[PDB]
Amino acid sequence: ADTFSMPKHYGKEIVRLHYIPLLDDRNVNDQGIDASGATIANGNLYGSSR
Amino acid sequence: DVGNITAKMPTLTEIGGRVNRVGFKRVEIKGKLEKYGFFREYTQEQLDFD
Image (cartoon, rainbow over all chains, first blue to last red):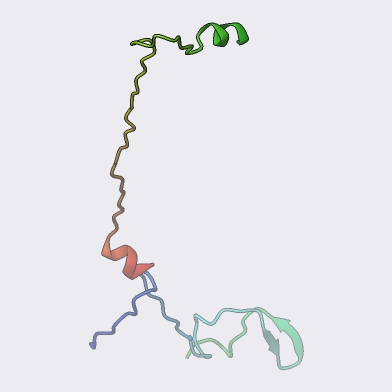
């Protein structure tokens, strides 16, 4: 790994964001519309089931 | 008081002599000096992380 440096006037803690790509089981939401309307639970395309 | 001043006036006679002597005086006035001060402390983490 490569070390990353922190600025001065920002406390003693750090934070970062992860974006969870679409076809993943962790992408849980309520924006799912089926192929004939009829809004459904899962907002992702068939999840990650293979 | 008129009576007291009239009674204690420095009257003089014809003969003269040692009849009216006076004197003077002086007094002192004093001063002073004093010292004052105050301080404060802090740490480096407070300066760097605020």
